[PDB]
Image (cartoon, rainbow over the protein chains, first blue to last red):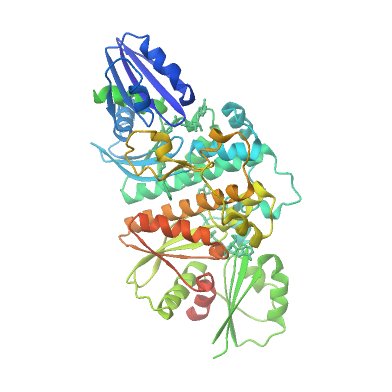
Length: 266
Length: 265
Ligand SMILES: Nc1ncnc2c1ncn2[C@@H]1O[C@H](COP(=O)(O)OP(=O)(O)OP(=O)(O)O)[C@@H](O)[C@H]1O
Ligand SMILES: Nc1ncnc2c1ncn2[C@@H]1O[C@H](COP(=O)(O)OP(=O)(O)O)[C@@H](O)[C@H]1O
Ligand SMILES: CC(C)(C)[C@@H](O)C(=O)NCCC(=O)NCc1ccc2c(c1)OCO2
Ligand SMILES: CC(C)(C)[C@@H](O)C(=O)NCCC(=O)NCc1ccc2c(c1)OCO2
């Protein structure tokens, strides 16, 4: 068997290949000791590593392992998954929405990193904690789907009132920009959490359409685990990608692009 | 006298000219008292811009020309840059207000090249949610000597002891260190420093991205979001220089739109 590991800041993504059967395992980066141990109990024909914690694994296992640069590995894996699922895209932006967010332009034969921003899943978790005292990711994300942003976010029509805006009125003018018009309010943990995800999705999508235009593609492929159990984030990103005339794509097992890629760079 | 007013989401910026200009600011909140002041005054020419120009116009008892904010801001900025001894053949400008709007100026005119709702309004609102402080002077002041280190995550923190493929001192995930420091103490300074951080960083990233697209090294930052907030100016200044671009701040750049309303007329 063959194993691929993308050991990120938050999640360790593991892909095992026997015959042609794939196994897709996720594990916490916090529990990296139990990944190293599992690995040490296994019969492995080939081990390929990538991600920020790849080296922690590599220095505590009993076998050699090839190590790849995660930008390369993610592009390779995502090419594999896009093909298999029927997407045949000449070019595209891809946005790896992980703990942080990295943005890449794939021109048809290779990738180039073209931007990055620190708004991603880490912010959802961290800023989510500070506003809700919720540490559990499922709990945090589920609760945010129950939320309404309208008392928190300020729209363009709120600013332009009864006059004609220079950009459409329903757009977000200012994330958290309505909070001070609603100080009579509670600000419920759900509402606050939807606004966090709101701001994270809008920033990511904004940067992505921006570089899409810069590199003259209209296809944007979103990946990373930040979308798992977060319909809200996936909605926010999708709607605004379409609103600005780009085509968004999500891919089955998108979050393992890295782990897959590492296997097929060997 | 001639009057130019940029009535924003949060602040109303007033410029009076006799001969010689006067700069004055008031809260959008208190728009009523701006209208009262316009109504008692003899004015040769009143020019309006911004989202609340309409609210002004329909409550004043005199006529008023209304100009579009992006054109006016561009025009006033050009004027202010020149008066302050700059000759930039082109530039990005980043109007950082309640929300942020980004423009490319090619030497003759401006195009909007994007925008983002991370801006002064988010500082105020998210900073209220993290701290319960509503007074702006106070909010921005608490932030100034905060420490972001237990809150933000650097690339070096993800990459541990191996060589990262981008510089390790870079922020990797805003608020991304929070869960590794659950052992109390998120203080209001550190939290507010982190809000400013994320807003400075998002704004600048957008700015330098459009600066590359449009092939200019010059980025001019305006808006009242920089008032009483050295840390926002620092965060933005440093990341811009990091990315190869030249940052510029402009004395009274918050009044760009007000000034421009007067000289499009
Ligand atoms: N079970 C989970 N526990 C914690 N976070 C989760 C979970 N499932 C999804 N997430 C989300 O996924 C995000 C991380 O996604 P991902 O696996 O792409 O990042 P990473 O590769 O660990 O980080 P990076 O590659 O930026 O170092 C988390 O911050 C969180 O928002
Ligand atoms: N005295 C103040 N009161 C409230 N907000 C202020 C003040 N001074 C600066 N600000 C900041 O500036 C922002 C407004 O920027 P501005 O350029 O005036 O935008 P707008 O045109 O939308 O009013 C506020 O969101 C706040 O962050
Ligand atoms: C694992 C990665 C680090 C590749 C991933 O999480 C990522 O790309 N994160 C975002 C990193 C980034 O590009 N940040 C942008 C940034 C923007 C502004 C900054 C800054 C950093 O440092 C200080 O000012
Ligand atoms: C006064 C203005 C509205 C001109 C100024 O505050 C501004 O330009 N704000 C930002 C508007 C913007 O470009 N927003 C970006 C945005 C990004 C994502 C969005 C979205 C809007 O609506 C829903 O998803």
